[PDB]
Amino acid sequence: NPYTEFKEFSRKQIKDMEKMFKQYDAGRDGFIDLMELKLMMEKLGAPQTHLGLKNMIKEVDEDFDSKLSFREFLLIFRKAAAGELQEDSGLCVLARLSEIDV
Ligand SMILES: [Ca+2]
Ligand SMILES: [Ca+2]
């Protein structure tokens, strides 16, 4: 339940993040993998290097399967709002360029 874990976000914000997550999960498997993340960053207008994509995932990949669950996607926005993302890092750019202002 993301609504009890991520209290810093409104329901509308979480739903918007859910909508974006689902947009880029091309295979409907419930995850964003590296290839899917590559495509998302391309379509946001800020393509990332292969290693940069890997490092983006690694920062929030709590179950070490090299792909992002919806919970881990939310962790990106939590980190952005906790002041923990490095200036102009891939994750910072993702959070900025999404329509979601946390
Ligand atoms: Ca997927
Ligand atoms: Ca994972």
Image (spheres, rainbow, N blue to C red):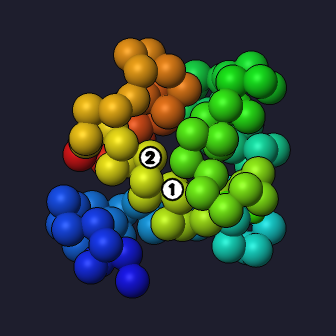
- Quarter assignment of residue 39: top right
Q: Mark 2 vs ligand 2: CB under 8 Å?
A: no
Q: Is residue 56 left or right of residue 16?
A: right
Q: What residue do we see at 73% from left, 73% from top?
A: 28
Say which residue label 2 marks.
76
Disc 1 crowd, CA 10 A, few/some/many (<14, 14-19, 20+): many
Amino acid type indicated by mark 1: Phe
Q: Quadrant of residue 4?
A: bottom left
User: In this rendering, does residue 46 appear at all?
Assistant: yes
Q: Which secondary structure, mark 2?
A: helix
* Residue 43 in view, yes or no: no
Vertical comparison of 30 with 89: above or below: below
Residue under numbered circle 1: 73
Q: What residue is drawn where x is 44% and y is 46%?
A: 76
Judged from the image, the quadrant occupied by ligand 2 is bottom right
- Mark 1: which secondary structure? helix
Nearer the observer, 88 or 44: 88
Q: Position of residue 12 (x, y in %)?
A: 24, 68
Residue at 69% in and 24% down: 52
Residue 25 percent across, percent down from the top left: 68, 62
